[PDB]
Image 1 (tube, helix red, strand yellow):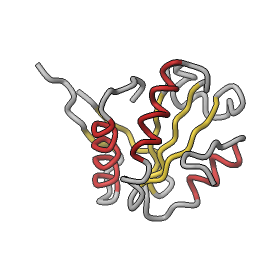
Image 2 (cartoon, helix red, strand yellow; image 1 turned 180 degrees about the horizontal axis):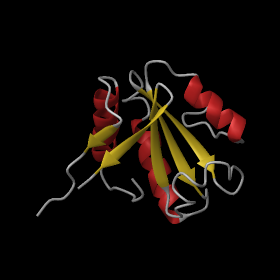
Image 3 (cartoon, helix red, strand yellow; image 1 turned 135 degrees about the vertical axis):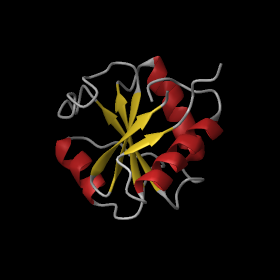
Image 4 (cartoon, one colour; image 1 turned 180 degrees about the vertical axis):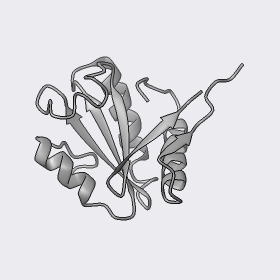
Length: 130
């Protein structure tokens, strides 16, 4: 009913997570008006179809839905969090920044999915070039 539906309260976020048995649930937490969220939403919308077989994306405004603000601490910048089979999946980069390439976002989501489905609660995406 919208490429990237908005989850309007804690119950909806919980249901979005509990509702997927085989795909990573990608959730953007931030302020809808924030410049970082605009850039993040643009990328996510542009790759939503591409990752559909293994990931589903949702948007959450943290002013409206403050419930999970202890998970990133209302980090502030726009952040994306990942869940697979009801487990929060951690990523070590060696996701709260707008990336130019939408392919980079496809990469991280695919990396989280492929690692999480084999049992990992921690996945790594070496973004420490230099």
